[PDB]
Image 1 (cartoon, helix red, strand yellow):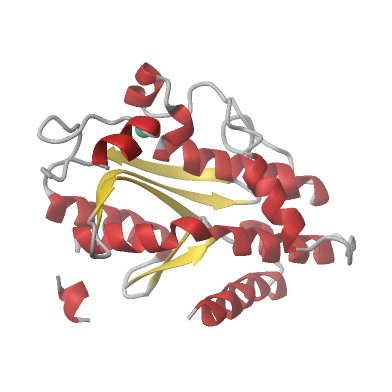
Image 2 (cartoon, rainbow, N blue to C red):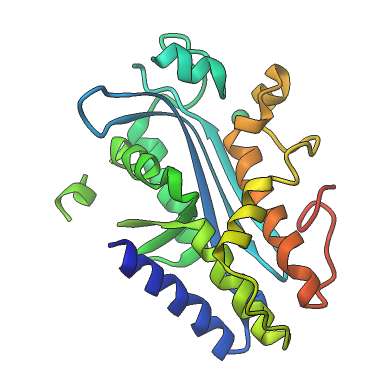
Length: 238
Ligand SMILES: [Zn+2]
């Protein structure tokens, strides 16, 4: 449930704080683009994926990024956002089974094997991201990746950072942290999109750019409370 997700995020962050390793807690951010959504069913057809692993101390530690060719409204959503070419001329990995395995391999290298995997994405994108993972599938069907709210993470993380920094502020609430996240202050950073999206100037809607911007947003919102040396590329734009 969403209530459950929220309590779980709070517990994750508090585990880190209590171990005195909040700055080293690692979080994986994910972003999907989709070509279109089935009219009657919860089926989003994936077009692009990125993931990154982030900690306050190290900033971006790794990034995984790929265009997706699923083979096949589609025109409108796609043309106004990512504008990736539609099937049968779509770019990217066309082996969906291989893609999913490669994504899980990446998440497992980050989080460990034999564990439920946890990733974060904007609240308004959770349904879509789960649907895209399902499209890519399964032993997973019969039975894996929990998709949590990155904005709730930002909120809880900011409050616990401020507690640690002896900076508690009753006036900082989730309206404020949501506002900061949605400002997208690093939208116009050069060189963080994939090559296609640099070519077609739709970097705003590039998954690789998006997970990088979210990382820079976390750093800008919190690393100042913590006396962490920010690193070019990793914490802030190169
Ligand atoms: Zn892209």
